[PDB]
Amino acid sequence: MALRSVGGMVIESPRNETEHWLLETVGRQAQQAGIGMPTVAIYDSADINAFATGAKRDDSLVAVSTGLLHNMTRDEAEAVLAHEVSHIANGDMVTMTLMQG
Amino acid sequence: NASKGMALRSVGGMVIESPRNETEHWLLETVGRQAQQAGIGMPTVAIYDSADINAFATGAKDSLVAVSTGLLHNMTRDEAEAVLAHEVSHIANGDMVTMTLMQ
Ligand SMILES: [Cl-]
Ligand code: NA
Ligand code: NA
Image 1 (cartoon, rainbow over the protein chains, first blue to last red):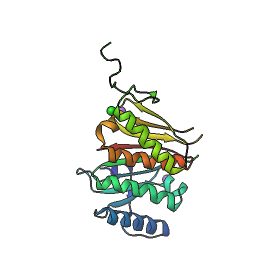
Image 2: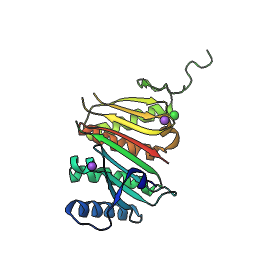
Image 3: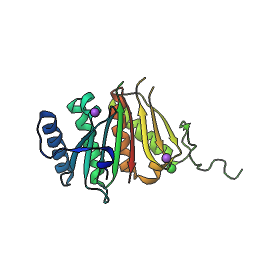
Image 4: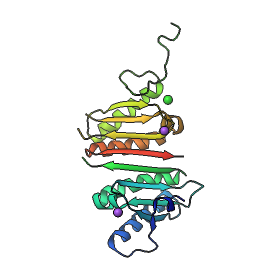
């Protein structure tokens, strides 16, 4: 439900540099946090947002907005994702929204 | 008259100057340490009343960090410290951030 309700679109295998980077980044962070690979999705929003859940209720998931991928550098986005993966590992849902100054 | 000098409940929406209770002291100390480590000035810190678990911050100008009572009720010190450290990193970049948890 966490994905469907936002119209999130799952990346099943990487087909461009952005998908490759997102999967490898989340994969490395999940590995380091001692958890299974989450489903990874992109959804449409102008906001710079990522949300993630490792709650019992949900399939494990990391979803990033198109606005995040458009506006964040890889280094910036990797920091946000690493923090959200820490919440998944805690069995929580997290959403974070940023605005650049 | 009985309550004068005792630890008091945080006032939602009030900027924290002199801690009213031990959580306020911990919050100033934690944010102060993170700010020092990130190389920025001490943010203004406030607690606001909400059942939602949220902290937000802005470093666009100096900065402010605002934490919900829901967050303080629901997160351990280590968990809250990690959220605050992450938000301080955004302030240090001159950015603004808001983060909400559903536990
Ligand atoms: Cl409290
Ligand atoms: Na879009
Ligand atoms: Na609320």
